[PDB]
Amino acid sequence: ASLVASIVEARKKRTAKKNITPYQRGIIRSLILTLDCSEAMLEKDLRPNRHAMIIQYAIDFVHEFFDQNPISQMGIIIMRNGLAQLVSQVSGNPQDHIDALKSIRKQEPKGNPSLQNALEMARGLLLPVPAHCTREVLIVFGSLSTTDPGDIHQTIDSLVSEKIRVKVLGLSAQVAICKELCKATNYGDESFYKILLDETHLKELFNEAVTPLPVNKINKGFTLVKMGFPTRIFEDTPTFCSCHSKLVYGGYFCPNCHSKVCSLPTVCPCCDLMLILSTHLARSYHHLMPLKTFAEVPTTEKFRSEDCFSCQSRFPILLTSSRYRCEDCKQEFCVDCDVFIHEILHNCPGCESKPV
Amino acid sequence: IKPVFERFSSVIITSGTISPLDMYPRMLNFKTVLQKSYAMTLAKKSFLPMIITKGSDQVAISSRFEIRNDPSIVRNYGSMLVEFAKITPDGMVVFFPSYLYMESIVSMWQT
Amino acid sequence: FIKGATISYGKVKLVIKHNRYFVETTQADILQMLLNDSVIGVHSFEIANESVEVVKKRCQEIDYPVLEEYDFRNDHRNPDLDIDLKPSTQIRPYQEKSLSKMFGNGRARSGIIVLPCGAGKTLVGITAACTIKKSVIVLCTSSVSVMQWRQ
Ligand SMILES: Nc1ncnc2c1ncn2[C@@H]1O[C@H](COP(=O)(O)OP(=O)(O)O)[C@@H](O)[C@H]1O
Ligand code: BEF
Ligand SMILES: [Zn+2]
Ligand SMILES: [Zn+2]
Ligand SMILES: [Zn+2]
Ligand SMILES: [Zn+2]
Image (tube, rainbow over all chains, first blue to last red; front, side, top):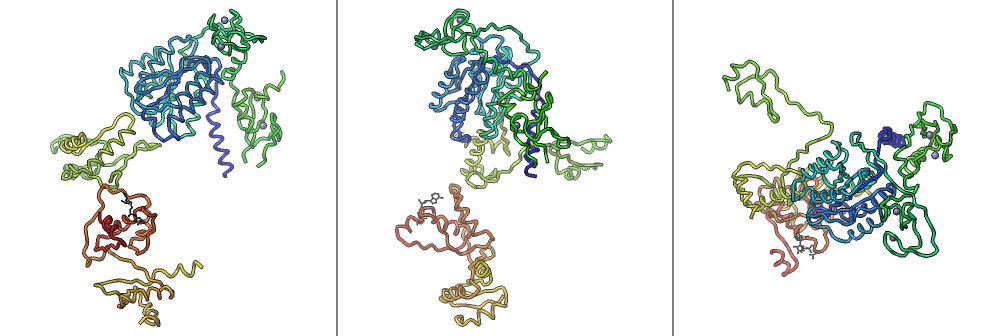
């Protein structure tokens, strides 16, 4: 029964994954990461302290966010002494944000938090953003009280008018404003206010936010974005960079003005034209054509082969069939591949192998 | 209330915390065809009723009028108020046995 | 090894009344054993106060040892003293555990308590006197200690 207990738990876990449909998602994103650094964050519920762990997870989130969203930009804000402090301008450089967070890791948190101040700063920082981008705000709230100079309700209404989206991660309990902020800002959806239940659960919540959020049907904006694909060039002598004005061995050449840049993907400093590589767009393709989840094969029927199609792993004999088939191509797979094919890869080998 | 129960044939007495139900017919001279209390069939527990008999120092706490100005009890109740206010997210309601007891104890906390 | 020594406890009780020591037993069968012992000399018989150290050691050699249990709840002859720990007191977790091992059954047991130096062995004795609420005597093997013990 112990082995069956694990199997049934896997089925329950697979129950949520069954319902997958290609929802429209905004690949281009503009995130404003807000961290709470107040007296309430000095507690020891999270070892060594809330501030240390949150900063540590923030660095991991930055690494993950830019890895799967190469054509996105992020900004970092912090609440301290009842005021909102800006620590990094919105930019596409992952290193800049990580460096800023590392410096923040030293200063001790103190004072009270001010959501209205943080939201107001986020609203201003997101004002110079193209309409084709999705404006998102990730707030890490730990305090159960908010001290603000003005009316928070007015700011929430302004946030809705600006088509901003807010995600709040709590630490202790539910806050009335956070629920209202996460509800009115997300078309009444109540799934954008999450409270962690332990140290491990917090890691999943940060990882979940990486995936682009689906867009609402009524909030439909379609437009064409002008972009360019620079060609990498190797130079025998170092030359000045158009971005930092420093000696570098070489850089990508913009196809619109021939101005060189250090690293990609970034907007050209001269023609203000977003420069990217073919790989950068390719990564976000899986969010557009998600691989249909595999359905477990009942043991009543007869299996095709005793070994996995993609990894040639003999299926254990052991109650419950250890095989998962793909409806599109009807190819059995072991448990290990399905996790690997839906988390690392995003293409079913069986479907590709089938000729037409 | 006697005229009311005689002039009207059918009367329903309902409330959220009317218990025990046997006493009201005794206190007010009337008879009921049926008297029952319904228990909520909530899937998940929604309210946590708990009773506190002593403070953090293991000292019994009570609101007896004669010992209202008790240095030990006042601190114990004061500690309870502050500690709960730290974890209560939005709102907290405190109910005192009488205005005078509340009036005196609040002054003690202020000093 | 466990069987031999684990069955001995709990058959003979020593009680004190009006400064007179009575070896009280709740069964009459013990009379044929204790009274017939060469060293010795519901039924209860008197015994010399100075002879307690002799019979008790003899009780170890013989199968049944003696236990010193005091039923202070039902002892009304001895005058009582009303003393309780003040609110400022804070019983540490280990102090409570030691008391539980003594009052687990419900009857006070005479024994030894071993705590680290400075852990509060004084308060251990203070708690026993306070909870018993009867006449108590304290012996402290020093003069400076007695002064600080009282303070
Ligand atoms: N519960 C307690 N609260 C405060 N101080 C305590 C407590 N228990 C013991 N102490 C302190 O421990 C010290 C040593 O106590 P004492 O009884 O002399 O220890 P011991 O006899 O085990 O050497 C004293 O300063 C005493 O006040
Ligand atoms: F063990 Be103590 F110093 F009496
Ligand atoms: Zn440069
Ligand atoms: Zn250019
Ligand atoms: Zn496999
Ligand atoms: Zn397939």
